[PDB]
Image (cartoon, rainbow, N blue to C red; front, top):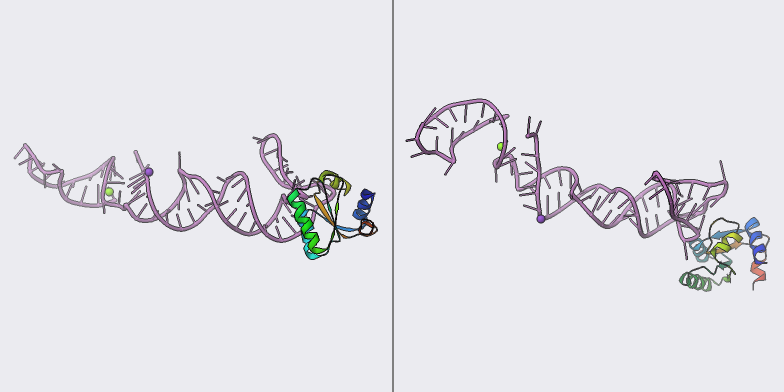
Length: 97
RNA sequence: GUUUAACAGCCUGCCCACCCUGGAAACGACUCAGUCGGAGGUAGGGUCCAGCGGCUGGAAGAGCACCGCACGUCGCGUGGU
Ligand SMILES: [K+]
Ligand SMILES: [Mg+2]
């Protein structure tokens, strides 16, 4: 399940939550996978997709809104998008492709 | 009774709004009340907006108060604080 893998990444991996940090990781090429929620504004989603295409980074469309993504990440706030800098014990980067 | 107009310049910069750095749970900030924050808070530094705000020019030469000299019939006279 995507949620279980995300929880495993949260408890054992490196990540950044938020649009600005996601763009920073994409610019720095440190991010390896970008997750975008349905709630994400269309323009922001398009910009993130363009950045990921430029950086050759996979993009996954989370099956939920920002509230659901934040809940899956274990946080009490909304998460519009997140970047997986390093999956510790998970294999999302390997399973998704 | 012990005053300072329009207008010109400089300064200031309410409550908001906005920008840059950064990335937050042991959640924090915060109002009389609320509310705000990974759609980026707290924090640090800035931009802008109001003013019937400040200083200067206008403008002390004016106005007001007080104290005097003089013509003493007609100087709307003359001086000081
Ligand atoms: K006027
Ligand atoms: Mg005088």
